[PDB]
Image (tube, rainbow over all chains, first blue to last red; front, side, top):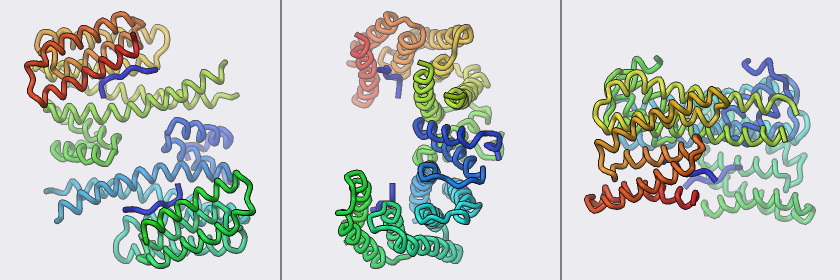
Length: 7
Length: 7
Length: 231
Length: 231
């Protein structure tokens, strides 16, 4: 699953 | 509120 | 145009890929290219054309309503809100004129079977409806008449040639009812058409398979949702 | 370019309207026009530039991943899947090159304060990162080095000039950590940077107001979400 970058 | 047209 | 060098089968394949990728502007350009090959569309291909343009114009309509609401507030500042609403409006008009042009060159002329002719006349009514949503004054009157006329021709073929549960016939009646309520200021005609359509479909469900029953009842629930909103 | 005749203030006003309308391609064209006026951007205007292009490239990246997955499946048919993936790839490259060009002409050169310089160097790292996601082979190596370099210059200024809770510094560390994990094949560097960033911010929260506390803890939760995923 892909990690969170800044929203 | 807006009515539903065909989706 | 720009898709003239691509094979018809490759345009249809790429329209399907664009749908999976949620690239609806690309999907619409591929389906326009496919229509411009000059051949009739199959049922699946008509669906791809409708999905593509409905998603493109749906984003435009949503943006237009946000901008129109801000413009109305600002008139209860500068020209920028009006200019930008006009920009989005003109782009939406252009998409509707493109779809209308495909229907007039030459999808409706070559459509002889009821399922294809009703589908295209319904789409003609829908895109004139979207033009009417942003039109003012006398312009508005002629655009409203063009919508009404397309929907009425579609309704007359659908009542003669299709059972009352046919999903195309149901979706036409749903959208014509929305026309009457929102565009033609005829709420009583809207409610009457939604109720008669729902009741006539209910009486024909006994004839359907499980899959056809699910298709027809899904659209009937939209009719019921609008009757709940309106009554 | 095409926005050369519009006032800078009108471009910023229309970028805000486009955001409200969820018209992010228009928002990005307006903000490009504003950057091309040649003046520095305020904090709010830097945010508008980042929101616009992040939403445009985010749709492109999502579409590219869907198409890349179908292409990989089809190689476990014809040229169409590769061609369409290439079309979306080239459009995504073009958006990244446009943003990189704005940063190089001349936003980074004129950015002297840490909040503006770190913001722009972070954005340089992010768009080289998005280029790296679709790059292969030796091309990939030079693009990865360009990302890493931009992020490292941003990190060195942020550690000297900003407190450990500063939201710009936090978001830089978050994204550089994602670079290390997903692009540079350095999961241990990714985990170390996320953990050190989180722990140093936690120790500085006592200095913050209610509003600054909410801003810093929101980004800290993204660091914690990635550490949960990775460990």
